[PDB]
Image (cartoon, grey):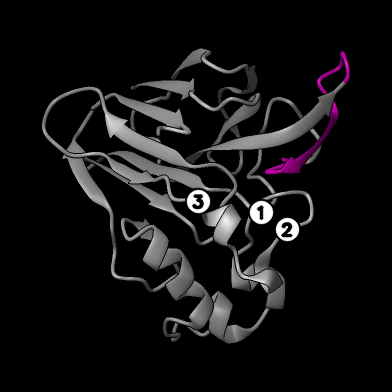
Amino acid sequence: ATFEIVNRCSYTVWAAASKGDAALDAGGRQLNSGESWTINVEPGTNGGKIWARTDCYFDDSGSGICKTGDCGGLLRCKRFGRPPTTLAEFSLNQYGKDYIDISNIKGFNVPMDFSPTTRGCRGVRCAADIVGQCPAKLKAPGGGCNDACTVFQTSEYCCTTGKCGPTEYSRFFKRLCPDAFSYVLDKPTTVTCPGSSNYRVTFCPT
């Protein structure tokens, strides 16, 4: 499947793409404002994620640090990034269908649209100003708005027992971005697309 990753933000982002135990495609790249990066994701990929990283410094070996979404200090991510990270999540060719969602379960750093470029399903978006409106206790100094599990590490926020409810913090994210997951047991906002669809992830869509 083809994903075009577009940075419409006014600032540089370092896109990342991983399935948690390996990079997808090159795994990461710098995107200046307006740039587009096209990646190929193997059919059958289960549990892939794309996200943006902000305020990164990398050396010539591709080693460094980012203030949001850092993936063990690498330009080319092999593992998932450190919160806060708005996530585009996908599983492809699962019994004939692709499944896509946006999640705020690991917080929010950059607004995002995640849409098919082929026919037969809808896109999803979280483009509200979550950072600006972030509750004081969830604000990340490096930038972004952490989820409550990351911050407080309780069974209730992290849904460790598999039983948890919405919280004051999850409802913040859900009010601003209803079409994104706000906590682990949120009513799913997954979109079902035809198997082998192609997609575009746009940072700062509005």
Q: Amino acid at mark 3?
A: Asp
**Could you tell me how far apart the alpha carbons at marks 1 and 3 are, in whole angstroms?**
17 Å
**Is residue 11 highlighted in magenta?**
no
Give the quarter of the figure containing the C terminus. top left
Tell me the crowding category of disc 1: few under 14, some 14 to 19, or many 20 or more residues within 10 angstroms, Cα based.
many
Identify residue for label 2: 140
According to the image, label 1 marks what residue? 83
Q: Is the residue 40 above or below the residue 64 in the image?
A: above
Q: Nearer the viewer, mark 1 or mark 3?
A: 3
Q: The residue tagged with tag 3: helix, strand or loop?
A: loop
| Lower sequence index among marks 1 and 3 | 1
Circles 2 and 1: CB distance less than 8 Å?
Answer: yes
Query: What residue range appears in magenta?
Result: 59-71
Answer yes or no: is residue 59 visible: yes
**Quarter of the image holding residue 59?**
top right
Kindly identify which residue carries mark 3: 129
Q: Disc 2 versus disc 1: distance between alpha carbons?
A: 9 Å
Q: Amino acid at mark 2?
A: Ala
Compared with 156, 59 (above or below) is above
Mark 2 vs mark 3: which is more N-terminal? Answer: 3
Please tell me how crowded label 3 is: few (under 14), some (14-19), or many (20+) other residues with Cα within 10 Å: some
Q: Is residue 67 magenta?
A: yes
In the picture, residue 77 is in which quadrant? top right
Question: Vertical placement of 72 versus 74: above or below?
Answer: below
